[PDB]
Image (tube, rainbow, N blue to C red):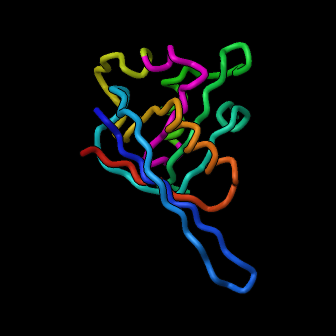
Amino acid sequence: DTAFVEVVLFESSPNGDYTTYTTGLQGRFSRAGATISAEGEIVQMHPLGLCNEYGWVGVVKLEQPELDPSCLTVLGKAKRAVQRGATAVIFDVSENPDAIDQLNQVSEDPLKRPVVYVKGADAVKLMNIVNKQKVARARIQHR
């Protein structure tokens, strides 16, 4: 059930030195996807792109439905990311609890990549890194 996510942020200096920062956070593998390990560069998926290269980890921050005018269901968003070559997708479900119920419905034919959700302090930590818009990678593991 539990998904352990390691996030690494890369920052380069003009002189060519680089720094990294790694932190850990926890989520859950949803039944909509696989419970396997995955790792890749983080790409945030915003609404316009969802409604319009490979191995990236997609991050989707769900908003309240009234503020998240969408073309897709939460499942449909996961499917689209996997279609477009994501190795995994992580939903921040902080502002939309119901998405958890939708992702956990027993699928006859679940996605073959992990579909993880985070919330609370773990989601805050993730989004604080994602919003910096630098190079960052996520590793997802089940223990």
Question: How far across and how far down the image is residue 65, in percent?
Answer: 66, 15
Coordinates of residue 54 in the picture (x, y in percent)? 50, 55
Quadrant for the C terminus, please: top left
Placement of 15 over or under 93, stated as above or below = below
Q: Quadrant of the N terminus?
A: top left
Look at the image and say whether residue 139 sits in the magenta stretch: no
Seen from the viewer's position, the closer of residues 112 and 58 is 58
- Residue at image position (70%, 32%) is 47
* Range covered by the magenta-colored residues: 84-100
Q: Which quarter of the figure has residue 100?
A: top left
Residue name at image x 41 percent, y 54 percent: 139
The residue lying at 70 percent from left, 21 percent from top is 68
Residue at the limit of the structure toward the left, as seen here: 143
* In-front residue for pair 11/71: 11
Residue 94 falls inside the magenta stretch = yes
Q: Position of residue 16 (x, y in %)?
A: 67, 84
Q: Position of residue 74 (x, y in %)?
A: 53, 23
The furthest residue to the bottom: 15
The residue depicted at 63 percent of the width and 40 percent of the height is 45
Residue 30: quarter of image: top left
- The image shows a total of numbered marks equal to 0
